[PDB]
Each structure stands twice: as C-alpha cells, then as structure tokens.
Image (cartoon, rainbow over all chains, first blue to last red; front, top):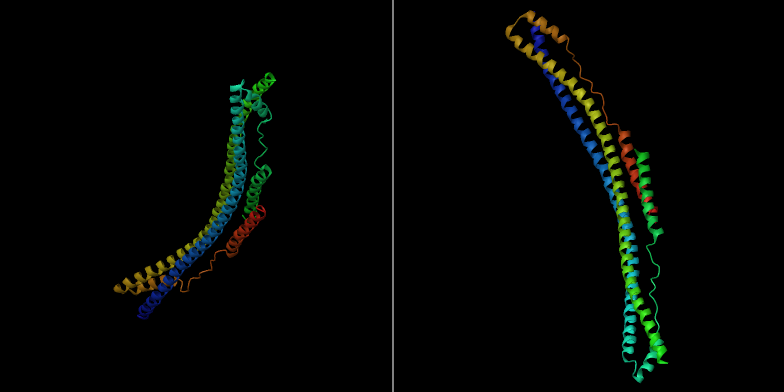
Length: 162
Length: 164
C-alpha cells in the first residue's frame, strides 16, 4: 500500500539525477559545437593566409615586370635625349655659318672678301640624321603575352584544385 | 671671279636656311617620338596591371568559394548537434515535468494518484541518451587546405619560369 509512495520518493531521487545527466549532455553538445566553430575558423584563417601570400607573389612579379618595361622606356627616351643634344648643336653651328656667310656678303667689294669668300665655300654642311631607335617590341610583347600565359595557367590551376 | 663666288654663297645660304628648318623639324620630331614612347610604355604597364587585377579577382573567387565549402560543413555538423540538442531537451523536459507532477501530487496522497503517476514513470526511459559521434569531415577539409597550398606552390613556380 504505502510501499508505492516510498517507491515514488526514491524515483524522484533518481529522476533528479537523470536531469543532471541530461543537462551535462546538453552542455556537452553546446561545447562540441563551439569546438567545431573554432576549428572551422582556424582552417579558414589558414587558407586566408595562403591567398594573402599568393597576392604578395603576384604583386612582386607585377612590379618586377613593370619596372622592366619602364627601364626600356627610359632607355629609349635617353637615346633621344642624346639625339636632341646632337641636333641642337648642328642647328646652332649651321646658324653660325649662315651668319658668317651672310655678313661676308655685307662687304662684297672690299679686296678682303675674295679671300674670306673662298674660305667659306670650303665649309660645307649637311642635314641632320635621326638614327633609328625604338622600344624593343619583342621584349615588351614577350612580357605582355607572358603575363597572360601566367593568368591562364593560374586559371587552369584554380581549375584542378577546385 | 667674284661673280661666281657670291652666287655660290647665295645658293649656300638657301641650302643652309633650309637645313636649319630641317633641324627644327628634326627636334620636334624627336620630342614627338618621345611622347609616343611614353604613351606606348604607359599603355603596356596599364595593360600589364589589368592582368594582375584580373588574376586577383580569380584568386579572390577560389578563396571565397573554398571558404564557403568549409563553412557549409561547419553548418552541416552543427545542424546534427542541433538535432541532438533537440532530442536531449525534450528528454529533460518530459522528466522535469513528471518530477513536478509527482511532487505536487504527494501533497494530495491519493494511492490512485500514485498508481497513475507510477504508470507515467514506466513510460519514461531510464537509460542514458546516445550521443553519436559527429565530426567535421576531415578528409574534405585537409583536402582543401593542402590543395590551396598545391596552388600557391604551382603559382610560385609559374611566376618563376614565366619571369626568367
């Protein structure tokens, strides 16, 4: 009769323990869930680094190429600077001989002219000669294409990994 | 005599005067070839620059497209745990309820009340709950992580030879 009530009392006690078992288990799951979140982020942060480091490498080759192009630009515009120099001289010197020859025929009838005149006939001049210079187009093309040949091979790697 | 000389000079002067303009035209010519050289260089930098921008867009996809794949798995697994939590909470509740019921019932002291509360307790499991093991798929993740390294290295090696 009253055995039933006392069984219930004891059961109550066991229940209390089951509840905690459940509460431990619930906390346990919430914690395995965080661990999982941590390990994910970890691996994302890891793969994020690769790409950063990839970008550093691309950024070098880009700069290193750019410079190679600019070095050529500079190479060539230097040659022209040297040609410019040479041409200005040619101009001013020819200018001087014009000025000489002209002011010589100022005084055509002095006896001294026939002497000065024949001297100036020996002083001949000639046009200015731009030599052929240009940007090395094979070198540049070579690069431009070649950086494409990278893009495409980077594309094809992103292929097989993904 | 002096007839011929002066006339030679006249002709010379006009050869010269014209060569002076040749020289000024030649000077303008080089300044213009220099701009052209500047324009063509810049073009080619600006073009080289675009490749790399486009390269970066491609790297930026794969990166995000991989990241998602990892996050999708995270979600996959935390969903399984959500389902386990659900199972466990429902257990806790059924028990906690029946404790509260049985408890306030001992106020009243009806041995039928008891028989009933006894039969309710027979329909509640007495065993632990079975947490199965849920794991992030490690092959899938390693697979990626290493594989993005396998990219870095092959991108490095392209940049090598495609730069010497």
